[PDB]
Length: 89
Image 1 (cartoon, rainbow, N blue to C red):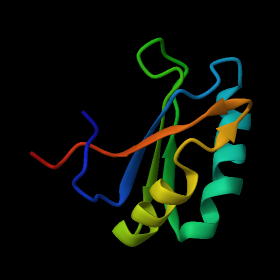
Image 2 (tube, rainbow, N blue to C red):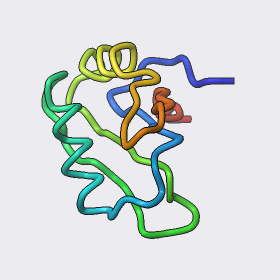
Image 3 (cartoon, helix red, strand yellow):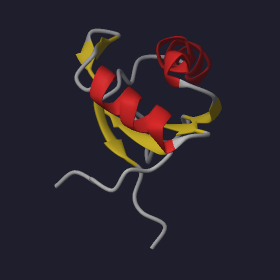
């Protein structure tokens, strides 16, 4: 059940786990900067957050535009799964 409450942060799933944090960040920034100001991009070197990223936009509308635009966009040969970050509560 996807998160549907619009949020300035997008949760991205199903990313290619063979890519170095530093390359993935640079490549996410390249495809997401179009939608507006990115505050940060969180990827981890964990087993908890491996095929997973947070793109934190300044504006919710940036996030909504990035979500619709890039839903299923093939990135390192895998369609990205994008939802809104979980709500404040």
